[PDB]
Length: 132
DNA sequence: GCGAACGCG
DNA sequence: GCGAACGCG
Ligand SMILES: [Mg+2]
Image (cartoon, rainbow, N blue to C red; front, side, top):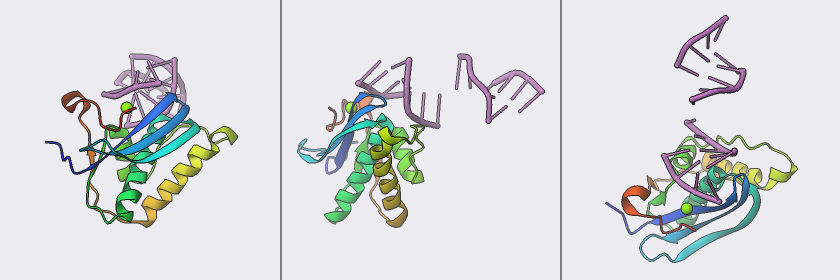
């Protein structure tokens, strides 16, 4: 069933592409462990990808073997493949989201981890604790 | 390759 | 309606 000793991440989108925020919380308590301030233009899947990679970096900094829960099977696969397969144009308006994605891919390409990245089963378990 | 035909905000 | 992931020549 649920591994309560874990990190849960999720994205808050206003439009898609549109304003992106994300956060990571303690699955057990809902305590906010990290939060990303609004990024003016991104896609939902780019935000979910960034949330998982921020989680990987957060747990590594703290010598944690906790798994990560995401409700985004798309983003879980992007992280496994070390590539965010986004369609979003690269122009002046999207430079920030793409800089963050490119830096996240660089991190994945230059680090190893054991962190399990698990699917949060929303239908079966209810909303992920990191939900906005 | 051409375009059609989950889990949101 | 968005970003994701067939038959035909
Ligand atoms: Mg959510």
